[PDB]
Amino acid sequence: FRKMAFPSGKVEGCMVQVTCGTTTLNGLWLDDVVYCPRHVICTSEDMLNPNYEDLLIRKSNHNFLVQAGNVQLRVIGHSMQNCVLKLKVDTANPKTPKYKFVRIQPGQTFSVLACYNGSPSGVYQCAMRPNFTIKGSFLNGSCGSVGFNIDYDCVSFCYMHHMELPTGVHAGTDLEGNFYGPFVDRQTAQAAGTDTTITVNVLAWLYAAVINGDRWFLNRFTTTLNDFNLVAMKYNYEPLTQDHVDILGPLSAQTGIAVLDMCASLKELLQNGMNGRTILGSALLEDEFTPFDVVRQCSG
Amino acid sequence: FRKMAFPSGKVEGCMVQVTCGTTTLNGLWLDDVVYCPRHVICTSEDMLNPNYEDLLIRKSNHNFLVQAGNVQLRVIGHSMQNCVLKLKVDTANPKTPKYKFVRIQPGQTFSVLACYNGSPSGVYQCAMRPNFTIKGSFLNGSCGSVGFNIDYDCVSFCYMHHMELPTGVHAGTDLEGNFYGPFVDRQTAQAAGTDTTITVNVLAWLYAAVINGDRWFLNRFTTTLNDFNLVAMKYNYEPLTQDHVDILGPLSAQTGIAVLDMCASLKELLQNGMNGRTILGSALLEDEFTPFDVVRQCSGVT
Image (spheres, rainbow over the protein chains, first blue to last red):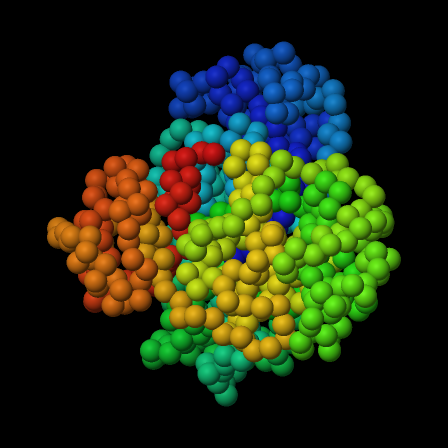
């Protein structure tokens, strides 16, 4: 198994840079709109307690420097939607792919294209933690970098980068400017809540182990969803939702192992450990491979 | 700190589909030449023991179906360079980036753009193991996928995929068709030499663990370079050269730990183990991060 990003070319052709004053961050150029974090309009002094509405009325279209490479795109309109600034430009991006804006659930994975001054720098796979942070690599200048999934040439944009917390994890919004988690875009003290293990992803990882012939951990037991949920939280695991059981369906069908039987197998691992043994060459359970990631790597 | 591949857009624009007989795989389209693994001309029975020069002379340009997305490209010439086939086409790739063919050294890393039927599907980092295999993710149809590094706007192609060994590791060639390792393009069981751990990479990754706040493995002790290499050879780690020591300099200076100080810490880890602890989340010593990979993601912003 390997963490695998989506090919980043379709997103690369949409990365621009947006500058106000001396603050330059990344923007996403789709059709004739550029999307970027709204704190590009902030000086450092009012970053402490931004009145974004008041700061925005004092800004005009001519205050925004949008550049594809070093080519300026003229701004003809500006608006603010939640924590995201939308800059209408006079040129429709000829590299605009088929796209959607979606809001992902915790545990879902996506590829991040880390950018600096509009230039793509690297691509890697992230998982949205249950505490709504991501463990990624975001240096200063990465604000405005986006996270995405691709399904049949359609780019689902799901993340835009805004913030790094004291513990080094990162936080941001969807493409409608709504933060994942209880974070606000201001230089104040903010803390990530306590994180938990993504149970649906651990179950997917166990299914991948079974597909590969590593199945010593399968037991004769079963369980109810509610009983597993109550036991799992005692080990700081996420409770399983409706959609979690459903998205495990394909793997349950591929292996013939009922979802609730696999839950009983994971429950035994939590209660008794792995008594020295290994799973897919590891005495650690992995929780950042989704069921879709599993079919994408075990199957075609 | 995590494995980061280069943006793949420049390579995606070069991937095409190449078909000969019942075999479909990927090709790399640069200027008016498409490069692809030469076993695309082999039937499944040819695969068992091919005489490649003989099998090629019996092929015509028209036996090669090349597809770039929806459009077919006409083959007007074909030649063979070692294990790589070069198909000349009537059209030049307008998306051809500035590029080079390089053969990388063991221990170095590169980004792999996994492709199927000429369509890119994923991108990830791989390291050329000392035994000249790579631990990749390649399924049926991934042959012709390339590995590369990007410096500014220059794509340095270094790998093209050919094979999966019985152990699950992968083997391929450079873009001149020469295999990494003692492998040959045949349907015959082949094992690799004994793999060793990339020592200079483990140290850089231990440094990254400190730039990122994890210091538990350190110790107040030190070691000579030769005494470290004696222990390292015992545990099947590659030797650490003075060139390796110099390369870790920026990482050593960026933190407060001399290289030989970190060598003493690695020596202790190899002699005791990690006693159920983790380093950067991992339960094992990672060796697929080069010192260059560490400096870029630890305050590099490139």
